Structures are given as C-alpha cells and as structure tokens.
Image: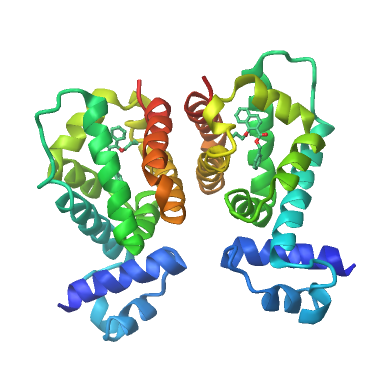
Length: 183
Length: 183
Ligand SMILES: C=CCCOc1c(C(=O)OCc2ccccc2)ccc2ccccc12
Ligand SMILES: C=CCCOc1c(C(=O)OCc2ccccc2)ccc2ccccc12
C-alpha cells in the first residue's frame, strides 16, 4: 500500500522533476510525511535502487506471457523485446521516463545490477550473445543502457506523435539500435 | 535587442519547459509584453522556425574557424563535427536541449529545411556523402535527426557527470552513432 504508493509517487516525481526529486514531495503526494518514507527506504539511494528493480520487473511482466523462447536468433528475440519495451513505454510514460533516469544514475549498486541479471536471465543470456563487450563492462555498461534508452525514447516520441507510421519508426529505431550496440 | 532577447528566452523556455513553451513566459522573460512578441514572430511556428535557424547558425560558428577542409574521409570529418557538437552542447546545454526539441518538431517547414542546407553546404555534402538514404528522406529525416541528437545528448550527459572518462564517451558515442546512421 504505502510502500508502492511511495513507489508510484516516486515514479511520477522522478519522471517529471528528475531524480533530484524531493523526498518531501514524493512522500506528500503518496499521502504520507517525509518521516514515513525513510523507514521503508533507509536512504534516497535505497529508494532509487529498488524502484529501478520494481520498474524493471514491471517491464518484464508486460512481456513474459507473450515471450516465446523458440527463437534462437538473437536479433529476432531482441526485436520482440524491443517492440515490447516501446509499447510498454507508450502505455505508461512515467514508468519509462523514471527508469531512464534511474538506469543512468550513479546510485545503482551491483546488487541492483546483479539482481537485475538474476531476475531476468533471458536478457542477460541475450546480452551476452549479441551486445558489444564494451557495453557490458562495469565501466561503460551504464552508458550502453543510456544509448539504449535514448534510441528507445526517440522511437516512442515519433511513434506516439505519428501513430500511422509508428510501425516503421519501431523497425528503423530497432535497426539503428542493433547495429549501434551489437557485434 | 528585443528579438534576440525573445530568441534567448525562447531558447531557455523551450529547452526547459519543452516546445509547449508559452508565448506568455517567453515574452515575460524577455522583458516585453505578449503583443511585442508577435510583431517579431507572426506565429509561434515562426518563432520555432527562426529559433531553429538561429541555433543552427550558432552551432556552425562554433566550428567553422576550427574547421579543416583538408580531410576527404567522411568518418574523420564527421568525427570533428561530432566532437564539435558535443563541446558546443556541454558549453550551451539550453541551446542543445532547445534545438533537439525544434529539430524533431512538426512545425519546421522545408523553407527552414532548405535554408539549413544552403546555409551549411558542407554538412549537406557530408550528409549526402555517408548517411543512410532513409534517414535523409523527407519522411524519416526528422527521425534520423532525433536518433541523431539522442545519442549526442547521452554522450554529453555522461561526459559532464564523469569528466575523467569524457574522451572515451565521445568516441564511443560517435562510433555507436556512426554504425547506426551510416551505410
Ligand atoms: C547495454 C545496452 C543494451 C541493454 O539492453 C539490452 C539488454 C538489457 O538487458 O537491457 C538492460 C536494460 C536496462 C534498463 C532498462 C531496460 C533494459 C539485453 C539484451 C539486449 C540485446 C540487444 C540490445 C540491447 C539489449
Ligand atoms: C540524419 C541525421 C544526421 C544528422 O547529422 C549529420 C549531418 C547534419 O547535417 O545534421 C543536421 C543537424 C540537424 C539537427 C541538429 C544538428 C544537425 C551531416 C552529416 C552527418 C554525417 C554523419 C552522421 C550525421 C550527420
């Protein structure tokens, strides 16, 4: 209740006013005081880190029922995942704008980064089969995610403003992402 | 005086509050009335179209003194231009964030799109020398610019937050852009 009301309030605030979102206004619009929100998340970095995983799991539950592991070709599996992310972002923009801020933020730990891989081995397995090895390194992985989500957000924006041509924007966006970020 | 103040307020407002920026808040931040603004831009689309050209000409003057025309290899000339844009954006974040909104906006006419090409034949010639044919077509050109400026914005953001690795972000950003947007 109040922990996910905070998680949904943090989503709204971080998507709008950035990750420099006040702990006060995240609390106040979740119908609580600032004191309330810090015994469920010790620090603002702990709120960031589990919201990122919460949003990550929300993206995966939108997809795994439609997910078909028959595909062995990395590019066709990435395309299904790419198509699903864009649709996920179009349906709930705040969840996308928030996860884009959290993914490229310094506050993320590798218990956030190694749980995110354990939570979703299929993506891990896929990344470890196509993505450029430099965008998997601890040093530049966040940058790849930033490139990543920049190409996706641009694809969303043209797909939502020009719905009649959305399908071509998804394909073009995917191909630009694919040759940019894979071997 | 007043029109360059309108253009600089429009630069601030469109980069900050998006391209849905009120003529009210553009005017009030230029120290003028709402009436005065429409004697320098007939319509808000004229403000958009003339700000885009103003910002385009500002970006090119940051580069043309350092521009070396010796190089005939497209990738080395695009890298100098890419390196120049990133530095331009780091020095003027509002001017970059604004031109990103204007470049992907429906309000831009071809009379702006043909001025941008006549004003900068080297960019046109270089674009007409390496870029994928579909990202130059009238239909998906704005999309190419968006993918474009999305990769650049991600490069700026990681370069400004992690300065010690900035040089690596510029090269990686450029190469990811290059294989994404060229043949
Ligand atoms: C490094 C840049 C890419 C991270 O993308 C990808 C992932 C992936 O695991 O993405 C992580 C992610 C982080 C934040 C939001 C959404 C996804 C997995 C497989 C991928 C296959 C091809 C391209 C991109 C892939
Ligand atoms: C299709 C997107 C490309 C826009 O980049 C480019 C230009 C160029 O002239 O881009 C125009 C521009 C538009 C908006 C803001 C800034 C520049 C010229 C040559 C290029 C060569 C390689 C890559 C990109 C290039």
